[PDB]
RNA sequence: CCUACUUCACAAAGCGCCUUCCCCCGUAAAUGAUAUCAUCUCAACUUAGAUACCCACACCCAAGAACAGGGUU
């Protein structure tokens, strides 16, 4: 999912800059996964 | 105040320290004495001189020609003392002035050889789609000088 | 002074060979020095029609250093005229194929865009290694000073240099590292 | 510092701490950069000043321990990044194209397949803008974008 | 003679022989030739500057397309220097 | 390079430069050592130029060339 | 490309026969700092990750519009 502004929606969601993009990675619900 | 030697502490152009004025005036006296003692004995060869005649400066060596774009109102063959000398150089020294060397130091003399017209110089104007088209021919007046002497006095 | 007419002219106009080491340097400071010397813009005899340009021998041009993400972000584009022959390669891929092409393309762009440009580009000799043919080493005259001052690493510092730099801070005694 | 020696017996031993050089020329500052008058006077080049502030595996030391200002910590952090990618700290490895002043990480930049028109060009960033406050020994300033 | 070089006016062949003899009159030993500068030496357009020396110091030097031409031309340059007829000689005082 | 001795005369209306000519030292000196297409390639690679300079040119172009041009100096 | 079949017939063809050789990058990992846990790292880092072809008169030709090319022992 590309979100131009990243939300968060659980504890486990965490923002990490990889490959030039901010991503929201999550482990409990991988549905949270986002991309700038 | 003290700064450790990093990349950008001391700027990359080299540090030169200006000498104190006492030994530097001693140095200047030594140099001027050398150059004047060359001039008194003729230790030079032939001279050139940058000379600010009609409106523009010429690098003038003795025995040569200079074409000047105006009529100088002098009869032909008539000697002239080109004042406004502003550099005089030899094989082993130069003397440049601020801006002009004194008249008491350098004499540059020339003659007027010939007093010609130039070639016909065409002045055409043209603007298109407008029937604008004009022609003129201008023959300018020119006088050719021959520079004889560049003599230098040892008055420094 | 006091030469004859033919040797005075021959001394004035005849061309000089300039070596130029290209290790660690960017290809545009090399290109700027070499372009000035290929045109003849380092001579007070310079005239555009005079054909007064000199010879330039740029060596070690495998060890060029673009100043930054240029090695991945600079693209060289060409188009073989066939439909679909548009080829863009980054500076890294172009450098891997032919390890001379980046300095040559930099120099080619710097030079004025007239018909002298390919006369000039033949006076230029680019070699990718330290190896230069012997028939060119016997012609060289000056080795031009490198345009980027190469900064040296931790391993190359002497002991006096390290001792001269102060330690700016006290670390706490109980610290893991 | 201390080290954790393991062999099975494991121990923690404090070993041979350095200490600051005696007289900071401008004491009673806050960060060690201030106390030696180096606020705007270094670059990515200088690997002594950068190498004092670095874990022996290339990582950089936290603010709360080394005592920097926030600004000079970010500056030294970016200068470490630009000194590692140029190949200036070879002793600090985690265990061949030549660069310097790389702002961004090398394997993660998409190339400029369409540099734009001149009035909206896509440029190549060079160096870091966190060093915008150094001394300018030039009239034409740092071109940070190429 | 204004602007005419000497050996446009006094045409000589074998200039080094005249120079060697002229140094024999001044009680000076034979001149040593020394290739001071050079360029393009293995190409079609060389440039050798050859200097004529007499006891560790040079009396003259001159350029040329080959070594022999530059050598004899340095000899002519020194011959202009010895006689006093250089290109910077004091102009004729009319 | 530059090795000159610069000075003012005492009043300060001229600048006197002393520049002698420096000779080359003896130590800094060496002793003297004692078809048509393929034609244009050989000449080009001899003289480091492109091929186009050696291709001939028309009678009309050769007929505008001035063969008694003015010399000087 | 023509051995067969087929149009055809000292050839040309398809409807017949033969040959056709390797990569695409976005993610998923391990070690690990700023931030002493952690973290794939627009931090230093470690994994999945081009050969071929070519190349010294005349007459006839499987070469050819002309020219060219090949052959004439
Ligand atoms: Zn501070």
Image (cartoon, coloured by chain):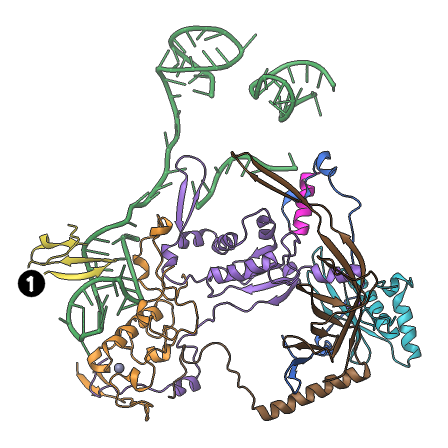
Chain colours: A yellow, B brown, C purple, D orange, E cyan, F blue, G green
For this rendering, which residue is in front, B88 or D9?
B88
Asked if residue D45 can be seen in this view, the reply is: yes
Q: Which residues are magenta?
A: F35-48
Q: Which residue is mark 1?
A: A11
Dividing the picture into quadrants, the one containing residue B9 is: bottom left
* F47 magenta-colored: yes
Q: Quadrant of the C terminus of chain C?
A: bottom left
Q: Main secondary structure of the magenta part?
A: helix
Q: Is residue D103 magenta?
A: no
Q: Is residue F34 above or below residue B42?
A: above
Residue toward you, D112 or E2:
E2
Q: Is residue D39 left or right of residue C111?
A: left
Q: Position of residue E81 (x, y in %)?
A: 84, 73
Q: Nearer the viewer, residue D5 or E54?
A: E54
Cβ at disc 1 under 8 Å from ligand 1: no
C58 vs D34, left or right, is: right
Find numbered disc 1 in the image and state the secondary structure of the residue it sits on: loop
Left/right placement of residue C32 relative to residue E14 reads: left
Q: Position of residue C9 (x, y in %)?
A: 74, 60
Quadrant holding ligand 1?
A: bottom left
User: In the picture, which quadrant includes the N terminus of chain C?
Assistant: bottom right
In the displayed structure, D57 sits above or below D127; it is below
Q: Is residue C156 above or below residue F39?
A: below
Tell me which chain the residue with mark 1 is part of: A
Instruction: Pick the residue in front: C114 or B31.
Output: B31
- Residue D20, position as x, y percentages in the image: 30, 89
For image coordinates 39% across by 37% down, the residue present is C84
Q: Position of residue C32 (x, y in %)?
A: 52, 60
């Amino acid at each position: 999912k590309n979100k131009t502004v990243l939300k968060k929606r659980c504890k486990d969601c965490y923002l990490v800059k990889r490959r030039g993009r901010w991503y929201v990675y999550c482990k409990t619900h991988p549905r949270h996964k986002q991309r700038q | 105040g003290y700064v450790p030697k990093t990349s950008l502490s001391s700027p990359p152009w080299p540090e030169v320290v200006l000498p104190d004025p006492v030994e530097e005036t001693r140095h200047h006296a030594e140099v001027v004495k050398k150059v004047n003692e060359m001039i008194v004995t003729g230790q030079y060869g032939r001279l050139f001189a940058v000379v600010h005649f009609a409106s523009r400066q010429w690098k003038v060596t003795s025995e040569d020609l200079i074409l000047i774009g105006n009529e100088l109102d002098l009869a032909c063959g008539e000697r002239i003392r080109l004042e406004k000398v502003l550099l005089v150089g030899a094989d082993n020294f130069t003397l440049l002035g601020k801006p002009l060397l004194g008249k008491d130091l350098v004499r540059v003399e020339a003659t007027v050889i010939e007093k010609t017209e130039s070639w016909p110089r065409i002045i055409m104007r043209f603007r298109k789609r407008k029937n604008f088209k004009k022609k003129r021919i201008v023959t300018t007046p020119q006088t050719v000088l021959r520079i004889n002497s560049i003599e230098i006095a040892p008055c420094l | 002074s006091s030469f004859s007419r033919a040797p005075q002219q021959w001394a004035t106009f005849a061309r000089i060979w300039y070596l130029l080491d290209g290790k660690m340097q960017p290809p545009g400071k090399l290109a700027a020095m070499a372009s000035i010397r290929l045109q003849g813009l380092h001579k007070p005899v310079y005239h555009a029609l005079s054909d007064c340009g000199d010879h330039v021998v740029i060596m070690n041009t495998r060890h060029i250093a673009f100043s930054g993400n240029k090695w991945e972000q600079k693209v060289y584009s060409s188009h073989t005229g066939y439909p679909g022959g548009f080829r863009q390669v980054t500076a890294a891929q172009l450098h891997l194929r032919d390890p001379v092409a980046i300095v040559k393309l930099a120099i080619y762009g710097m030079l004025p865009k007239n018909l002298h440009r390919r006369t000039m580009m033949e006076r230029l000799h680019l070699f990718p290694d330290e190896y230069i043919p012997e028939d060119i080493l016997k012609n060289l005259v000056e080795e031009l000073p490198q345009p980027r001052k190469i900064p040296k690493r931790l391993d190359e510092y002497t002991q006096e240099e390290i001792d001269a730099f102060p330690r700016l801070w006290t670390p706490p005694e109980d610290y893991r590292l | 510092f201390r080290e954790v020696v393991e062999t099975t017996i494991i121990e923690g031993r404090i070993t041979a701490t350095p200490k600051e050089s005696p007289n900071p020329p401008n004491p009673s500052g806050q960060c060690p950069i201030c106390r030696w008058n180096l606020k705007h006077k270094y670059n990515y080049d200088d690997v002594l000043l950068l190498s004092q502030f670095i874990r022996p595996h290339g990582g950089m030391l936290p603010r709360k321990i080394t005592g920097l200002c926030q600004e000079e910590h970010r500056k030294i952090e970016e200068c470490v990044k630009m000194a590692h990618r140029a190949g200036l700290l070879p002793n600090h490895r985690p265990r061949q194209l030549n660069r310097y002043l790389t702002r961004w990480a090398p394997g993660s930049v998409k190339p400029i397949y369409k540099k734009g028109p001149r009035w909206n060009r896509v440029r190549m960033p060079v160096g870091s803008p966190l060093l915008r406050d150094n001394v300018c020994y030039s009239r034409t300033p740092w071109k940070l974008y190429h | 003679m204004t602007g005419k070089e000497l050996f446009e006016m006094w045409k000589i062949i074998n200039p080094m022989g005249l120079l060697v003899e002229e140094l024999k009159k001044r009680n000076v030993s034979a001149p040593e030739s020394r290739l001071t500068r050079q360029s393009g030496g293995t190409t079609a357009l060389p440039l050798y500057f050859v200097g004529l020396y007499c006891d560790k110091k040079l009396i003259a030097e001159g350029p040329g397309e080959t070594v022999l031409v530059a050598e004899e031309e340095a000899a002519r340059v020194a011959l202009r220097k010895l006689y006093g007829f250089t290109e910077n000689r004091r102009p004729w005082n009319y | 390079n530059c090795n000159v001795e610069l000075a003012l005369t005492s009043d300060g209306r001229t600048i006197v430069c002393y520049h002698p000519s420096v000779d080359i030292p003896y130590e800094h000196t060496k002793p003297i050592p004692r078809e048509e297409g393929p034609m244009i390639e050989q000449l080009s690679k001899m003289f480091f130029t492109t091929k186009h300079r050696w291709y001939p040119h028309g009678r009309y172009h050769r007929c505008r060339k001035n063969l008694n041009p003015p010399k000087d100096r």
